[PDB]
Length: 192
Ligand SMILES: OC[C@H]1O[C@@H](O)[C@H](O)[C@@H](O)[C@@H]1O
Ligand SMILES: [Cl-]
Ligand SMILES: [Cl-]
Ligand SMILES: [Cl-]
Ligand SMILES: [Cl-]
Ligand SMILES: [Cl-]
Ligand SMILES: [Cl-]
Image (tube, rainbow, N blue to C red; front, side):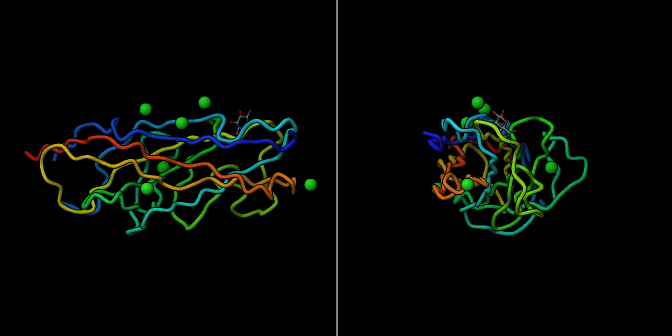
């Protein structure tokens, strides 16, 4: 069908955080390996102008200034810290369009357009017409309080969802949504 786009998750893995070798709160304690999915929305037979609105759905504890080593931003920005549920550990999130020239968008509001970033100040801006919508995902872990030594399990958490919007009413009205996931895993703290 013309509008038969279907969602697919985009996921990033706790298991890629290096060992945290250790006091200031909050502070970033490492970055996960950034991930990407070219086909978060895909499958409709008629090309469309599309955009993705990200809404985080974990508790927001506060803000921290940061500049991802990954991505190409040269200035620090404010990021919302989201509660993993594990005491002392939060995450911050950036997202971007799929292709490398689009900028990392810090998640620091209730919702934001991750691509095109122009849509945050122009409600009629969309990606150029094509058959898919993808994105890049960046996450860093944040010490929000004192951490014990040793291994810690992080549960799998849904960080939020991307809503597909379009200037084609029939596609926009479907309110297709795709999950943005933190795959759980183990981290290790070494307190010397
Ligand atoms: O840049 C807009 C879109 O271009 C397409 O060619 C890519 O497959 C999508 O991942 C991307 O969202
Ligand atoms: Cl993915
Ligand atoms: Cl990975
Ligand atoms: Cl992909
Ligand atoms: Cl950044
Ligand atoms: Cl969850
Ligand atoms: Cl229309």
